Length: 115
Length: 115
Length: 115
Length: 115
Image 1 (cartoon, one colour):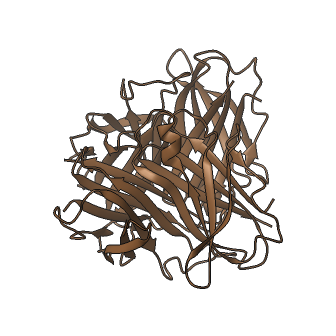
Image 2 (cartoon, chains in turn purple, red, yellow, blue; image 1 turned 135 degrees about the vertical axis):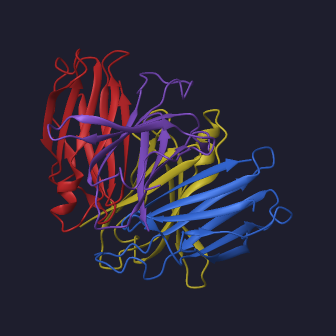
């Protein structure tokens, strides 16, 4: 499992459960082509997205699409979408973990690359 | 000024200077149309991107080109850029400030929305 | 103004107003001595905490009372406060801005240091 | 294992290995008494800090003390110390995970409370 995604909720202090996550890979014409996707588990994780053979070097984008996730106050609803764009590089560690922390008007993301 | 961007560098503890910023607006056909762009000043701020008349209701994408910034400082960053998608002026005209905090393998973006 | 504090609210997308802030300086006997305190303005900023003469070299602790802030808004936060310890003016006098971003179960603090 | 701590490095994109972490519990006289401590593992985690019987309600502080951790540039070295103060509450989930993301002039922390 070369690519793992973990989503957390900064308002509730818990994993972000059952949230849709999409991964795209950039094509020669600069178009974003679907690569893998799924919904986070009860631990806020998404495993089995891809395989070592399929996850080659290139530019990828991880989009997190929350829907009716906050269900709370919010004058001027932001409808925020985390959009994490990175380059997969073979010259570094092989395992990638993309973590995202969500709030109504903010988000933070970190990459943990290991072997 | 209805749309401003401020960027900070967490490694050097300073404003992020001369960072390129691109703003897009989603079109009817679902494609991203260029809206405005510029570069941060010595204070890490970018003003004058648009006007009240031009900044209509819609879905916007703010892309901060962090890879170029880190590389210009001799670092090898993980992300291509720091990006956030949101809906603006859906409850009437508002002033938006997108504040970003950058590190080589992590970043955060927050929106300050006022009347 | 050599020491300023700015606080933002990630749930409401606005400055954090009327937040109490306490600053301490470590004494010779290893205890924390009160240094300065105040509350953020309508812009979420706190100026005039100290002067160049009073802000000597040392180890400082900035405590932002986030529990009181969240509770005053009807929320039940996780942390007692947002705190950070650092060494100031160890390379000569500098201007410091401590910027904090708050959510009920998470927070971040960053320092902008200029000449 | 009611209390777990995970530390990440935002500059290197990896777990923060072999870093000293201290946990204190506030006493009646408002003094901070040592409670548990250790050094992070190769996964940046610290398990076995305490037991369900020992981890009672109260105010706790998690201090992260990095030493010669950055070993890089840094005019006006911040010598930052993450200080996470929270109240353990029995009316909520039983398992606590305190996560911290470190940078030279900034840090972020989040609490994930589950059952």
